[PDB]
Image (spheres, rainbow, N blue to C red):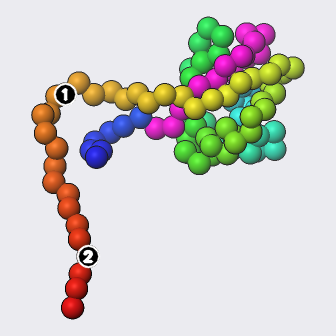
Amino acid sequence: GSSGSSGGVAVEVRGLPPAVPDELLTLYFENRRRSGGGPVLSWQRLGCGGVLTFREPADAERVLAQADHELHGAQLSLRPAPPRAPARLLLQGLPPGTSGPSSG
């Protein structure tokens, strides 16, 4: 069960050289010809990689689909990032939700 705001679509990027600017990193992913995704919401460059966010979920997958990724002479290892969203609450319990077939 979900309710409220929650993280969007993020993909964990691994094996990315610094010699390559984020600009390209996105340009590539954004390129439907090179990859086949769409617009990127945001990008978070980390040490040897960084977590990337794909505007669309399917699009994000459209890229992951490819186990191969090249950007400025280099092998980028894309993977499905883990879950994570902002929320600091603790509501003990859950809402209802039942169902059943019908008869005549």
Residue visible at 74% across and 39% down in the picture: 66
Span of residues in magenta: 8-23
Q: Which mark is residue 100?
A: none
Q: At numbered mark 1, what does the secondary structure look like: helix, strand or loop?
A: loop
Residue visible at 83% across and 19% down in the picture: 74
On the image, the x and y values in percent for residue 64 come to 67, 38
Residue visible at 64% across and 23% down in the picture: 13
Taking the magenta stretch, the answer to whether it contains residue 37 is no
To which residue does mark 1 refer?
A: 89
51 sits to left or right of 95: right
**Residue 72 in sight in this render:** yes
Determine the CA span between mark 1 and mark 2: 36 Å
Q: Quadrant of residue 11?
A: top right
Dot in front, 1 or 2:
2
Q: Which kind of residue does numbered mark 1 sit on? A: Leu
Q: Quadrant of residue 4?
A: top left
> Quick check: 2 above or below 49?
below
Q: Which kind of residue does numbered mark 2 sit on? A: Pro
Taking the magenta stretch, the answer to whether it contains residue 18 is yes
